[PDB]
Image: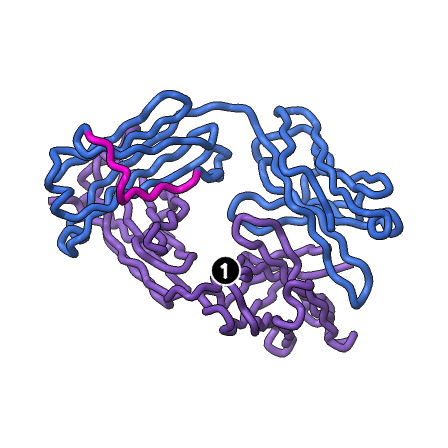
Amino acid sequence: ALTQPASVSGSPGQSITISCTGTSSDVGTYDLVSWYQQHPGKSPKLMIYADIKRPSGVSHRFSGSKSGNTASLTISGLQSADEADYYCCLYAGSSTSVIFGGGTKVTGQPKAAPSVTLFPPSSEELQANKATLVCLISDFYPGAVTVAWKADSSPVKAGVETTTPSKQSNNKYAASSYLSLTPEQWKSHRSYSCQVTHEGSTVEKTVAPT
Amino acid sequence: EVQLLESGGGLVKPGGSLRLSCEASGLTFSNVWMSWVRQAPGKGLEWVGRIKRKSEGATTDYGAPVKGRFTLSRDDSKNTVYLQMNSLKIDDTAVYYCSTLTRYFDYWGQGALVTVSSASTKGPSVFPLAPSSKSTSGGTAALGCLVKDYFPEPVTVSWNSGALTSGVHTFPAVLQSSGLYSLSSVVTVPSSSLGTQTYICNVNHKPSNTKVDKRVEPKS
């Protein structure tokens, strides 16, 4: 068992510490550990190993220290690109097993309003007797939106599928929402709206039968 | 460089079997230990197992939740490592990362997704999202294609067989109440009319051995 803090906030330019906490009969007695970086939807990467060392293909701002029970990772000069999940692990000799930490997150402090893209149902999908409205939210911060659908002026809860916000490669966030209708409902109403609320303001897109 | 690529991922029914394979390159297989680490969906890294080199007797060790149900195998003559999974359960659904072990984990593979589930495999329905100036909140027009009603993850998307990358924004999938996934890839573009420019999205749903190349045309 290895324990580490769920969340560790920090401002740009400064130095921050993550702790990997073990037990005396493991980390205390025999002091070795390795640390990993995992950006969203991507392979983990070896940052530091054997507590101290670091490959020449790694950024120098990552360093490892330790006490008896607990080894800790410190990051100096924080930037946007440091925003990832961070893990610690340990392996003993032969006839044993690797122990992994829980995984911790780091953070930044900008702000941005979403871009919203909205398409009606394709000609092909209508011909197939289905209809889907596609609503795509991108480049927003913080990673938190509300998506609401309106059929003309009337709210629609039914047939709505909305993703959770997800960290985008440019450090901002992205999300998507789909409204599923019957062709008869789609051509029934004068217009449909995808309404996205972020930090109190709303960006709204509209489509209509054409 | 060094490259590690996995394969054989996709869907398997609980109690069924699914073998993963992982090919090495830019590294001498013979002398390097191979390992698997598992990223359960929305959860942390859990170690699956390690397999020692031929010269040490090709010994193997596994994580407790795995031991007795998975068997880790090797083949240097074919330059690959095999992960065999016998007794499978919904708790095993995960991304499986092929990795090297050295005296920590130096090199990592792209990761294969195993979705243990009683649900059936379903290839996607793919529709073009017609180019429109009025589709975006922002200034420019956009077009894309809709990857609808597939199972399980993942699907990958290219445009013009990888030739088109700049305007391209592929979104994460939604899991629908229907138990099926839907995905969208949008491309930013100059105007609602696009004569002479070709826009074909390449949908690759490896889990269902399905691939769809959909061209997006102006709406009438």
Q: Quadrant of residue A190?
A: top left
Mark 1 belongs to chain = B
Residue in the picture at 15% in, 54% down? A129
Considering the image in quadrants, where does the C terminus of chain B appear?
top left
Q: Is residue A90 above or below residue B167?
A: below
The colour assigned to chain B within the rendered structure: purple
Q: Is residue B177 above or below residue B121?
A: above
Residue type at the position of mark 1: Leu
* Residue B166 covered by magenta stretch: no
Residue range of the region highlighted in magenta in the rendering:
A154-164
**Residue B8 x, y percent position in the rendering:** 49, 69
Q: Which chain is blue?
A: A
Q: Would residue B57 be seen by someone viewing this image from the given angle?
A: yes
Residue sitting nearer the eye, A93 or B176: B176
Mark 1 crowdedness (10 Å alpha carbons): few <14, some 14-19, many ≥20: many
Is A85 situated above or below A154? below
Decide which of A176, A160 is in the foreground and name it: A160
Residue A181 rendering spot, x and y as whole percentages: 20, 46
* Residue drawn where x is 69% and y is 55% of the image: B106
- Does residue B112 appear in this view? no
Left or right: B157 in relation to B52: left
Magenta stretch containing residue A160, yes or no? Answer: yes
Q: Position of residue B38 (x, y in %)?
A: 60, 58
Determine which residue is flagged by label 1.
B113
